[PDB]
Length: 115
Length: 115
Length: 120
Length: 115
Image (cartoon, rainbow over all chains, first blue to last red; front, side, top):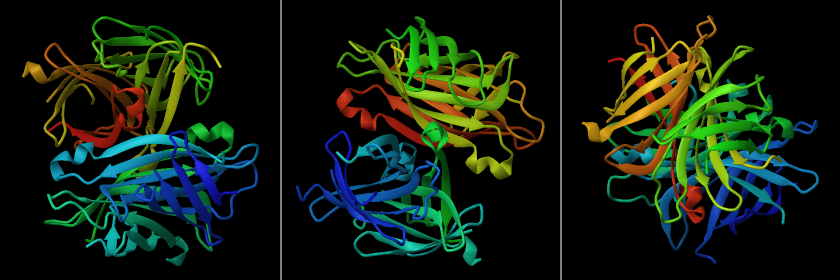
């Protein structure tokens, strides 16, 4: 259910493989200059009462072409069924000096679908 | 610098290895029954201006003894200096039904040190 | 056009008046949680926003205590109003329950709400 | 416990009156130029178990002299006694265009004391 290609509504696309050990690994494409490594974890033996599957991943925004000095972690759940969704909240953290530490983190949410 | 053993106020311990091209691997404990796998990423080429090093990691709270059907993601930055510390904000998502999604996700923060 | 009656995706109703001094005053009625009947709200908004088509920053608070019950908790919504055809307010919110020191790590929930003047 | 002047480590100062209704009213100072109105709510009947006292408040960052086109909300709790403190998580949202909303909200924490 998780393994595959997921789209948000801003044109972003990620491809993930959900491993039996509970590993999540893939590529987030914000172009080869826009592709980044993702890595995370998921609940590999979820409850079967209609609850969703807890998961999370991280992208550090560096590849072989560019570097944003920042990272995004998404925390959320997979909802199967009808048309599957991954509903998430995210944190974006940027490298800053001590003095700008207070404005280092952005918070948001994102929903991914299989189409 | 990142590589090593870290602690938080509440006495949890996390062991990381920072890979030369941005990977993070390790364990998070709070005894082996409290040991879980972490995985994440970091900026392997941070600014030279005194800024910190962005990073993130995830833990799914399942091991071979336990499953709380939830996962936590930490987004933050490593600050090398007088005292090396990792300053984070985090998100804990639980698997919930669609009716309870609204109360699925906790938010907090955590400071890690090597001491 | 912030003043008025607003609905979120889960059918909660927010009745608010935007005054001249940047004040936000009203009532909230939730469709979920340890809740029943109206709760008092107060907040602030930017009463002289930019012209560039940026939205209007705003915020408000509800403590979940009325004459019928007390959930020992408060939510704050932080967001922006976007005017026009289908007007709307997009928010991220934080819900803090009172806890003892030991349980404080789990005292805050975070979430996102979207309000529209039409009920879903 | 709550009415009076509170200070963060940042320097910022906030003076509040907690009314019997559960109203919070006051000013947030960082000179007139840096003074802003705050309004909020608190639980005027907290449990007795030793649970802190839930509150929140908002400041829109406009006064007669400047306008940042932004608003911050603090969600947190009051913990009384000698080292009485208010612990909060905050959100700061900036008015942005639709294209830019994904980066409109910052998150962080702050701790307020009486000294």
